[PDB]
Length: 7
Length: 7
Ligand SMILES: *[C@@H]1O[C@H](CO)[C@@H](O)[C@H](O)[C@H]1O[C@@H]1O[C@@H](C)[C@H](O)[C@@H](O)[C@H]1O
Ligand SMILES: *[C@@H]1O[C@H](CO)[C@@H](O)[C@H](O)[C@H]1O[C@@H]1O[C@@H](C)[C@H](O)[C@@H](O)[C@H]1O
Ligand SMILES: *[C@H]1C[C@](C)(N)[C@@H](O)[C@H](C)O1
Ligand SMILES: *[C@H]1C[C@](C)(N)[C@@H](O)[C@H](C)O1
View 1 (spheres, rainbow over the protein chains, first blue to last red):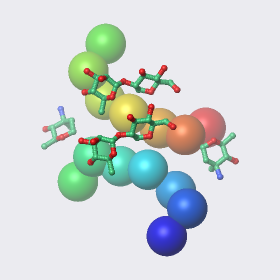
View 2 (tube, each protein chain N blue to C red):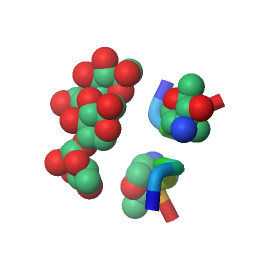
View 3 (spheres, chains in turn red, brown):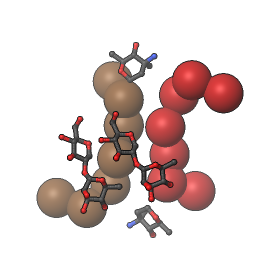
């Protein structure tokens, strides 16, 4: 909820 | 590249 990724 | 972030 306000960070990025991709997981 | 090919990863994401944000730093
Ligand atoms: C992710 O955030 C970046 C930087 O602000 C933005 O340029 C991208 O368009 C954004 O990606 C989209 O939204 C995310 C949630 C989806 O997983 C991705 O596939 C893309 O639609
Ligand atoms: C990824 O994030 C950068 C940096 O902020 C932004 O300038 C790019 O436009 C962003 O890439 C897009 O969104 C991702 C999720 C897609 O895989 C990529 O093809 C591109 O559309
Ligand atoms: C985001 C990019 C990635 C780490 N290369 C991919 O494996 C993941 C599913 O999406
Ligand atoms: C990506 C999002 C973030 C972690 N909130 C921000 O601090 C960074 C500069 O960009």
